[PDB]
Amino acid sequence: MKFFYSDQNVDSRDPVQLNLLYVQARDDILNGSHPVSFDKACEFAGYQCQIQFGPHNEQKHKPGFLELKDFLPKEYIKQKGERKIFMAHKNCGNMSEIEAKVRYVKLARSLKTYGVSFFLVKEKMKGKNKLVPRLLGITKECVMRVDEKTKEVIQEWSLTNIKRWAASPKSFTLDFGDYQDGYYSVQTTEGEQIAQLIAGYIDIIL
């Protein structure tokens, strides 16, 4: 099931409710709840700058001005994206605080990762001692594998195509029956939590 997001839903919000949506979307990105690419994180941060400081001011917003911890998810603090952030901030021109929050919320809703519950798991490659980290996302409609570093969506399965599933204290397993050869099984210490989430979306045969 493919959902279309409303553009008007965002614009029609009351300043109060808009701020509420913004804070929620912003916090999810900053705390890692909503995984985004480095480029996108800087784009969001640019809007955040416009919102917190007003129009970009070269006389004050110089290299080293930003506390990156407050503008980027932790995994990007080292890639030093202040340059990109300031470029996005400057690109906002004289955009109002309201317009910036609107674009922020729409940008978040435009991503395939929006509204997805993610878990960091490890995939095992046949005969290869070294695992491959991967973001496993779940929604009422689907399951998706996401690149841990780039956040590229590499695979998606409809939740209704899961024939059966299982969990253990060290793994999580999905069986799609004839849709593919073999299970999708990953190592994780959160398998039981993942299985419970899925059980809240699809019922179990008793």
Image (cartoon, grey):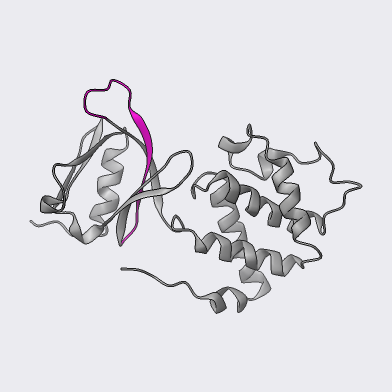
Which one is nearer the viewer's eye here, 14 or 125?
A: 125
Residue 19 visible? The answer is no
Instruction: Name the spot of residue 46 as percent of width and height, x first.
Output: 70, 53
Q: Is residue 150 left or right of residue 166?
A: right
The question of residue 127 being in magenta is answered with yes
Which one is nearer the viewer's eye here, 26 or 149?
A: 149
Q: Is residue 187 above or below residue 73?
A: above
Quarter placement of the N terminus: bottom left
In the displayed orientation, state which residue is furthest to the left.
206
In the displayed orientation, state which residue is furthest to the top.
129
Q: Is residue 18 left or right of residue 9?
A: right
Magenta highlight range: 125-140
Q: What residue appears at the point 58 percent right and 44 percent down from the top-left corner? A: 38
Instruction: Name the spot of residue 204 as percent of width and height, x first.
Output: 14, 56
In the displayed orientation, state which residue is furthest to the right.
59
Instruction: Name the spot of residue 65 as percent of width and height, x first.
Output: 81, 40
Quarter placement of the C terminus: bottom left
The question of residue 192 being in magenta is answered with no
Q: What residue appears at the point 21 percent right and 35 percent down from the top-left corner? A: 168
Q: What residue appears at the point 20 percent right and 61 percent down from the top-left corner? A: 160
Asked which quadrant contains residue 20, the reply is: bottom right
Q: Is residue 193 left or right of residue 6?
A: left
Residue 40 visible? The answer is yes
Q: Is residue 16 left or right of residue 130?
A: right
Q: What residue appears at the point 15 percent right and 53 percent down from the top-left corner? A: 179
Instruction: Name the spot of residue 40 as percent of width and height, x first.
Output: 58, 51
